[PDB]
Amino acid sequence: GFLEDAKTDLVLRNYYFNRDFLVDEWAQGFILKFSSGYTPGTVGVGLDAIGLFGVKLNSNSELLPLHDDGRAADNYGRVGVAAKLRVSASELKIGEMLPDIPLLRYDDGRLLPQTFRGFAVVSRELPGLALQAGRFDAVSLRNSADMQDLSAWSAPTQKSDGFNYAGAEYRFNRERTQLGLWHGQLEDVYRQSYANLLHKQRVGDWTLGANLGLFVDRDDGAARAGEIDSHTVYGLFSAGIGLHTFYLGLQKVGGDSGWQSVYGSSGRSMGNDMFNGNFTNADERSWQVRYDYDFVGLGWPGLIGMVRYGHGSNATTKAGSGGKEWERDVELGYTVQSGPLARLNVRLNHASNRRSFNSDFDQTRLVVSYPLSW
Ligand SMILES: COc1cc(C(=O)[O-])ccc1O
Ligand SMILES: COc1cc(C(=O)[O-])ccc1O
Image 1 (cartoon, protein in one colour):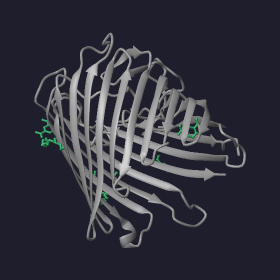
Image 2 (tube, rainbow, N blue to C red; image 1 turned 135 degrees about the vertical axis):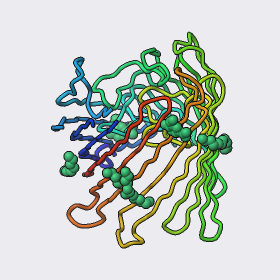
Image 3 (cartoon, helix red, strand yellow; image 1 turned 180 degrees about the horizontal axis):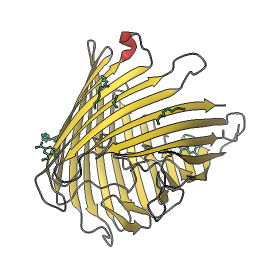
Image 4 (cartoon, rainbow, N blue to C red; image 1 turned 45 degrees about the vertical axis):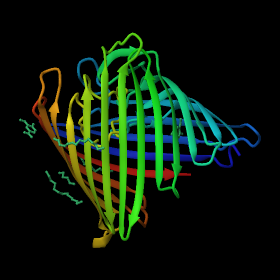
């Protein structure tokens, strides 16, 4: 039922951000999600809403929008609604939403999430197969209260009428393997095709995983961001045992151009994605090593750590070719497991970025999040 199965989730997010090239930002966010149930019947009808509000505290950062003078706003926010319709094992949503698909990953790396306006269909009528398609005609950046036309990261000022997509994922092999094929079009800017293989296998105490991906990009229509021709391949491999996980990522961009994506979106589909980049400049070859540990092994359940290092070379940018870069990320995340503060999450992380072709910097963040649900 519409009211029966309705859930309300509120997240309080206190976010401290520092980047030393020392500049600083501190802010408080509120993210309110109201998700109804579905009316009973052949066509079920529902409504989702999202409320976003951020407040500046005394002190990228992209935590808050900037005034024209370059001064961060005191506060910002917006409210979005989406209608939902369900039939059998298929759903259509229309309005404002948070798309999380391989060709369009909504960003939530700062204070409030990026949202999009459009429609999205998910259909699971055949066992193991999920079909998706949709179109988004406006976007609200993570650091904006407003909606604007979409554009590509490679030319953020060149606007498009919208982003269309369709894709399929098939999961099989006792749920161990998944294949994905996706096609997207940012109208008059670029078209992108993507293939993905996910696979996991247990060898004794080890869990071995692979995430292989291939993107192929070209300009579309009027080609407002210029001519584009790119392909990007990555393989991210994991080996887990007990409380430990090890990763090796390998990636290469080829062709005339870098890898394409929608401006403001997250780079997290890419194998070597890190906090401050994903090594997708034209021609760029990169590798990554990563280690994760679950500190329950030291009597600290709820505490998890990650360290990762990535290096890119052969990078072509406007300035020149043969560019090199590296990033090192470290994170400790703690989630309170029990007691009055249960579910409270504290994440502390640090990134060091060095680039032969751009500015070097270190970055420190502390994010304290508390979820309430009723
Ligand atoms: C528009 O409001 C919502 C959107 C979403 C989403 O798209 O994932 C989730 C919960 C919401 O309340
Ligand atoms: C000269 O600047 C850099 C060089 C390298 C390198 O040689 O691997 C890496 C990152 C840099 O920022």
